[PDB]
Image (cartoon, rainbow over the protein chains, first blue to last red):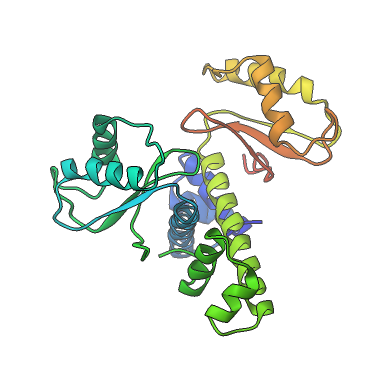
Length: 136
Length: 139
């Protein structure tokens, strides 16, 4: 059991096969507007689900450090490394790997944060980003 | 933002710091039963979210093959391998790697499946298992 209805999974699957919203509406015998709304609602539930798994894996993080809007991306690896020594736990990434990770996934605008976010280490030692700032 | 309330996030965090459900009930000033019911509902929503992402990546899967209750786990690599050549795409896993995956994750009872499930290849080329059989959705 999931957060998607059977109807939403069917529409998403038919979309994945390349069918237009108007084509799918005819197969299911409902308005094209209803199909568009149903697809939009499903994608929103998937994003909501994706953020939920992010908050769960963040709650169980080895080490997490917070980056504020406007900070420099290159100052971040030290923040993580300093807190990692405070907890005496190893961060299995070079300063460059952390940066190349932040370029691909962080809300940045050329080395500057455009929003607050937290960078953390997965329980599986993956690097991850979340936009929920948890107080501690 | 997500499917978790601010209350459920606080409780999960306190559990992750090792507290007992009764300790948490005191901190939030409510019954221990309420804390357990809120914690159970939160983990259930996380599993529900985890299954929603699986179905999403299954809908966009490279290659998928379906296995029914009673089939032999050892016949599965051939089904996947034949279906990958019909689509002319590579599966970066040996027959043994596929087997050792199904032993760890599939609903099997000694090399025989106790329920239907779908084995598929992630968009990131990971191996994955899902229990929703969506190949009927093809006409």
